[PDB]
Length: 165
RNA sequence: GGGAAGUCGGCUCCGUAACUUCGGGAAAAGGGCUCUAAGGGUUGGGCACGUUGGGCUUUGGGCGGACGC
Ligand SMILES: [Mg+2]
Image (tube, rainbow, N blue to C red; front, side, top):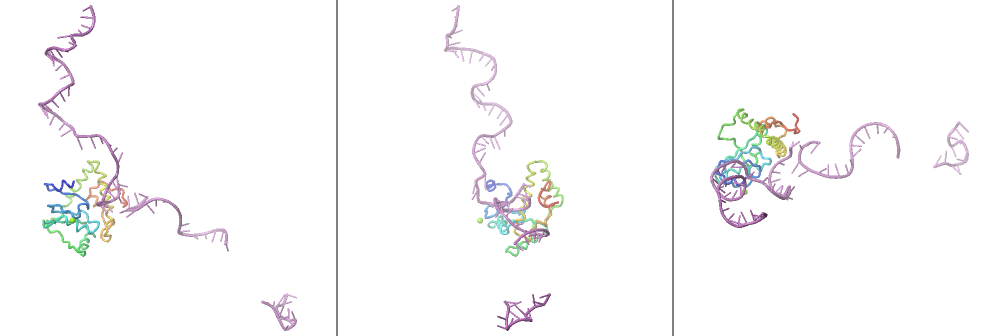
């Protein structure tokens, strides 16, 4: 899977964990996107650095949720690194017709049987990784809307995980 | 009865109210993070055509040249 990416002649994209997040000189790389905030802060600086290797203009972008994780920006600011809002493109998000794109993955959740427990197990491991976050003042396991996550991950039904609803 | 009035000279257990042991076990509770090794062995890649031979008839030869009379 690695060897097919380095000699790839197509606009490919890799979905990885923190394996490919440190010291990697992969040539002709431009975009890096953070779905999750890092579980530890030093990983962020190495995570952005997988875009702009020796000149070669690189875009680094991290998605965050509304709430106290908007306060994560000044966490970076005081440490050493400034953070600025995005500049281009300025189009923010597409509305609930993108939910009509987002709910599409719940359709193949019905179609394919194997993706069902794949959907659950991915979601709940995400919850386990949340309370391991070192920023106990920024990311809370209480101040998050589980329905918004379930719509985001396209969960068919919430698992029997210990937050009663 | 008096009280030295003699004479120098008498001094742990029962009932009631809270708390406690041994063993195993680090990481949500009782489908659950990152990375670093290892995480039992064996056997397993599709669909057609013209093509190779044996494999289904047909067409022939000799070898057997028999067996018995
Ligand atoms: Mg390096």
